[PDB]
Length: 160
Ligand SMILES: C[As](C)(=O)[O-]
Ligand SMILES: C[As](C)(=O)[O-]
Ligand SMILES: C[As](C)(=O)[O-]
Ligand SMILES: [Zn+2]
Ligand SMILES: [Zn+2]
Ligand SMILES: [Zn+2]
Ligand SMILES: [Zn+2]
Ligand SMILES: [Zn+2]
Ligand SMILES: [Zn+2]
Ligand SMILES: [Zn+2]
Ligand SMILES: [Zn+2]
Ligand SMILES: [Zn+2]
Ligand SMILES: [Zn+2]
Ligand SMILES: [Zn+2]
Ligand SMILES: [Zn+2]
Ligand SMILES: [Zn+2]
Image 1 (cartoon, rainbow, N blue to C red):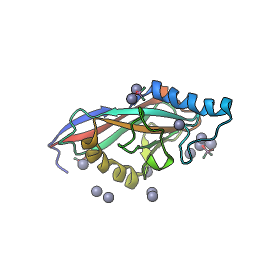
Image 2 (image 1 turned 60 degrees about the vertical axis):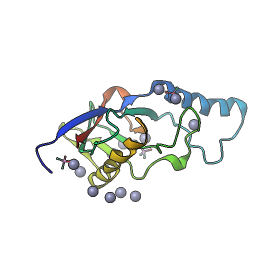
Image 3 (image 1 turned 45 degrees about the vertical axis):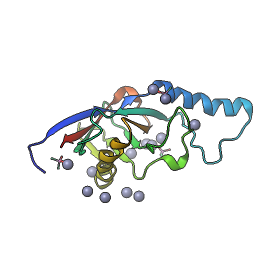
């Protein structure tokens, strides 16, 4: 908009503990032979839980994503209802957001690509979801050839 605005880049960091929580849960149901909680969303092996901590709940405007990969691959960052307390609820399929920001990189080059229109729609939303709580949770789906160790995934906001 304007080349003048202060920007704050906030990293989506790997949430190893809850990722595992979720990983053990899908087990459990296996060893127990119990079914899920009706509309419960079970973390697949290909997904990993990421965390985003909002440094300034207010005055965040969202500006652009800053996601890049090490190898050619694909990733999908599906947001999560800010009403989901991983301390309390079990993530419900319905708690996932629409849409998701899908990013990918093709073989020969280094240039990142994504689903623009959607990555922007989902984006403009973080500026408000920030005012709900200082913690945002996401579920990243890794393609083939990609694993957590190839990704940088911060979100750049504008300071109002
Ligand atoms: C300067 As802008 C269009 O990335 O909010
Ligand atoms: C889901 As937790 C163990 O980071 O409060
Ligand atoms: C071809 As696929 C949708 O199983 O990564
Ligand atoms: Zn944690
Ligand atoms: Zn679960
Ligand atoms: Zn902007
Ligand atoms: Zn592909
Ligand atoms: Zn917790
Ligand atoms: Zn849609
Ligand atoms: Zn494109
Ligand atoms: Zn779409
Ligand atoms: Zn818009
Ligand atoms: Zn819109
Ligand atoms: Zn896959
Ligand atoms: Zn695939
Ligand atoms: Zn393929």
